[PDB]
Length: 25
Image 1 (tube, rainbow, N blue to C red):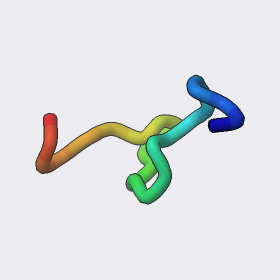
Image 2: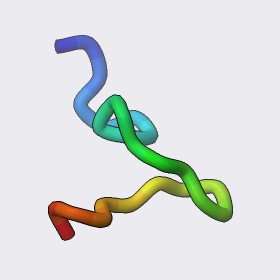
Image 3: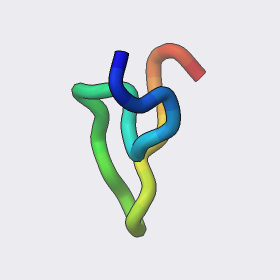
Image 4: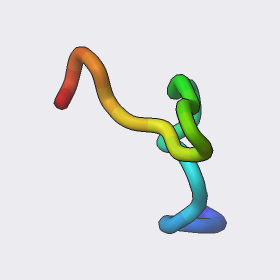
């Protein structure tokens, strides 16, 4: 691993500037 805290968990949808889970959370 290179970076634990980035932006998204790779393969997520972004909205308003930040991505969130739909089916998982």
